[PDB]
Image (cartoon, rainbow, N blue to C red; front, side, top):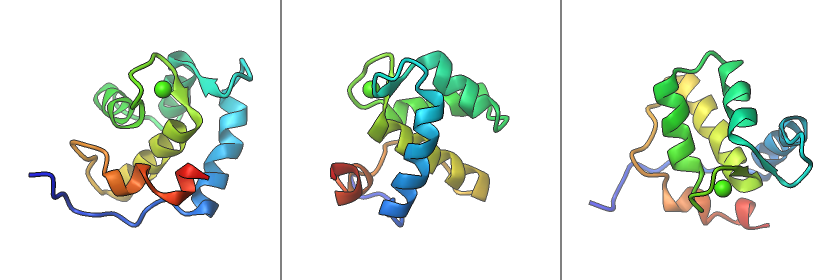
Length: 104
Ligand SMILES: [Ca+2]
């Protein structure tokens, strides 16, 4: 059901490590990155198109074409976890998104 295996959530240190990268990917300096920006970033990690869309699905909550700062941190989190061998959720855990690190 809504119970899913929990994850060690993003730390301020994780969010910060992602945020620096965000500045590098956000070429429009809008506070969001574009689909192209995001894909190219993830493609540099040699991620599959399947993972690419899946990470997007988990990250882009507000269903907009762009990955926002929070979402981006989520994306990279999922991506790092993916490379660690941990499978990508069918639904991004609420404890990850509603975590204080993404709130602050
Ligand atoms: Ca978004």
